[PDB]
Length: 9
Image 1 (cartoon, rainbow, N blue to C red):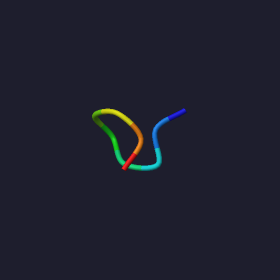
Image 2: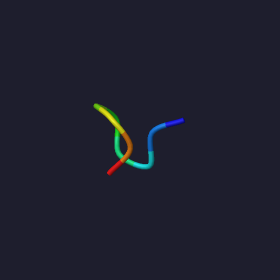
Image 3: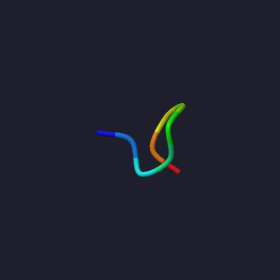
Image 4: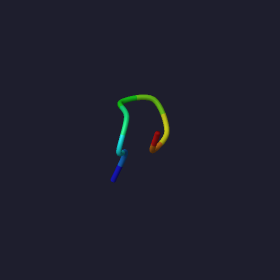
């Protein structure tokens, strides 16, 4: 999914 929280870090 997103390794970050807005795209995928």
